[PDB]
Image (cartoon, rainbow, N blue to C red):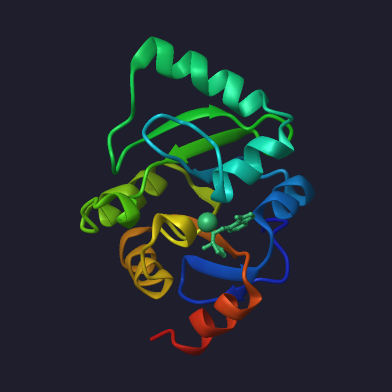
Length: 167
Ligand SMILES: Cc1c[nH]c2ncnc(NCC3(O)CCCC3)c12
Ligand SMILES: [Cl-]
């Protein structure tokens, strides 16, 4: 039993809800919130820009130190950093950004990072400003993640189409 509430169940292990991931994380304070990161951990917009804003830029400060030490992530890769006031940990996951010409096949590799965590709050990887089809992203999520994932979809109109088209 967990404190995730109001989710529609899609599979044994995948759940979904129309919700602002920022407001969800503050309410639940999950063990892991997933960020839709880029390789530079520059949290300028999208889910990443919103989460960082909610941390009063502490996420960005921590991220800049991480990059200065370790260099950029790989597309499809991840790192675990602090969750600040939103969660215990933030799993920064880099899905391919179609608006940069990045290979969409790397989306499966990106979702594989979720399997290292028993329970996560997460957005659809490569959706929104990363330019991929959110329906496809949901399919890859369901077919790749085996741990318990609570997907937050910000757009109510997008949320309804995702549910209404799920096979
Ligand atoms: C930008 C943002 C703020 N809070 C959020 N919570 C969950 N998802 C998000 N953006 C990913 C989308 O696919 C959902 C609708 C268009 C992009 C956000
Ligand atoms: Cl977005």
